[PDB]
Length: 400
Ligand SMILES: CC(=O)N[C@H]1[C@H](O[C@@H]2[C@@H](O)[C@H](O)O[C@H](CO)[C@@H]2O)O[C@H](CO)[C@@H](O)[C@@H]1O
Ligand SMILES: CC(=O)N[C@H]1[C@H](O[C@@H]2[C@@H](O)[C@H](O)O[C@H](CO)[C@@H]2O)O[C@H](CO)[C@@H](O)[C@@H]1O
Ligand SMILES: CC(=O)N[C@H]1[C@H](O[C@@H]2[C@@H](O)[C@H](O)O[C@H](CO)[C@@H]2O)O[C@H](CO)[C@@H](O)[C@@H]1O
Ligand SMILES: CC(=O)N[C@H]1[C@H](O[C@@H]2[C@@H](O)[C@H](O)O[C@H](CO)[C@@H]2O)O[C@H](CO)[C@@H](O)[C@@H]1O
Ligand SMILES: CC(=O)N[C@H]1[C@H](O[C@@H]2[C@@H](O)[C@H](O)O[C@H](CO)[C@@H]2O)O[C@H](CO)[C@@H](O)[C@@H]1O
Ligand SMILES: CC(=O)N[C@@H]1[C@@H](O)[C@H](O)[C@@H](CO)O[C@@H]1O
Ligand SMILES: [Ca+2]
Ligand SMILES: [Ca+2]
Ligand SMILES: [Ca+2]
Image (cartoon, rainbow, N blue to C red; front, side, top):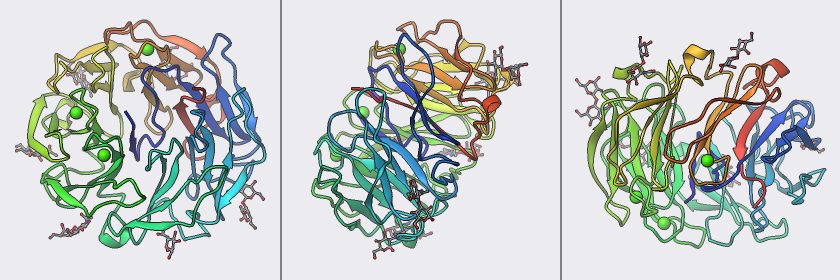
């Protein structure tokens, strides 16, 4: 089940044994999930010093652009889109190749502060197309294989800067809301959540308002205080809506056809009223049990809090599953990336954090409870010069 969000543009597999990837000063480095835990440099590019890559101008992702289920390195650079393909053996093509003179800072006028760039398999080809929410609307470049990307085309004249879409007010996602397996657009706009149905052919149907909530102008949902996710809360592979609001967690369940039901307060925690603050805490939805549905995970003050989904979008009690990864243990949103991702292959998401001095993990027992914290390795951390301003780090399934 693939959902692409602004916060998590690189989806991960359930089950999986996700790797760690880092775009450091000197290039691209990986920690292969395996019996030997080490940092390996794979490309002398896509780095602050290796190619002049900047977080304020360029976009760096992992995505399968060839169709072999081994994600490639994709960077939206200064004058075009650059790709280093995955060789399958802990190496990548170096140097990367320039596949399209668009979607770039000085080619097409793309801006981190104004626009969104994703890679997604929008036509079920098995290959990721380039997808951008730009000025005029959503632009796609078809991945025709073999490094051949077609000229960018307007997929739909909406969800663009020109239609009032703003990173400081609104949210945009790609997610299948119909069940046909095609990722549709989900946008939390000014006054409505809208969807736009993927027609399969590089176009989206007109925006349709589905929910008059979860937006700044409909309920007072703000970017700085009230995060929102799109995720399957029921198990039918159709995405639902979840928001962390003031009183707690609100949901709107998919009716099954890309229309959405009533908005309900389903849990009185993980909200502003329980102390949660975007500036100090991390809130995620991931599958932590064999039910294969969105459970709630929060990196709070004292540790990690979890509420398990009963299977139908209603939730059990909140339990502090570990007394670590929290604000009280030194964890800072502007320094220490945290992800909820299967690292062990059992289908139950685990925890990994890039800490001050070590990368730390903590493994799901298989039932949504967790074991003790493990120090994985002393690298890819603040202490080794990895900052949010100069580097990008992800959990990603590089080998499949
Ligand atoms: C960030 C980026 O795109 N780096 C690639 C580099 O891009 C340079 C631009 O940074 C510079 O402004 O202009 C030239 C065109 O004159 C390039 O497009 O190009 C490198 C290859 O020369 C590539 O390795 C970098 O990844
Ligand atoms: C950002 C956004 O939601 N854009 C949509 C646009 O939204 C406008 C608001 O920007 C404006 O503040 O108020 C009006 C209603 O009074 C709309 O909600 O509306 C468009 C028309 O539906 C839509 O296509 C844009 O995406
Ligand atoms: C962002 C959010 O939680 N919106 C929901 C709305 O929340 C308001 C608060 O914005 C305000 O601070 O406090 C009051 C209670 O006195 C509410 O909790 O509540 C709406 C339901 O009443 C809900 O639809 C909004 O999404
Ligand atoms: C943000 C957060 O962690 N909220 C949980 C709440 O945490 C509070 C702390 O915010 C505060 O600093 O101290 C008290 C204890 O002195 C709690 O740790 O704790 C709640 C109950 O455990 C939990 O429901 C909140 O989600
Ligand atoms: C944020 C983080 O890495 N927390 C772990 C903690 O790391 C600390 C740093 O917060 C501190 O600034 O430096 C010291 C060394 O003096 C540690 O590296 O270490 C804790 C246990 O060793 C761990 O539980 C925190 O998660
Ligand atoms: C930010 C943005 O949408 N840029 C697009 C660009 O990619 C596209 O090729 C061009 C075509 O007219 O128009 C805009 O300039
Ligand atoms: Ca669909
Ligand atoms: Ca569902
Ligand atoms: Ca696991």
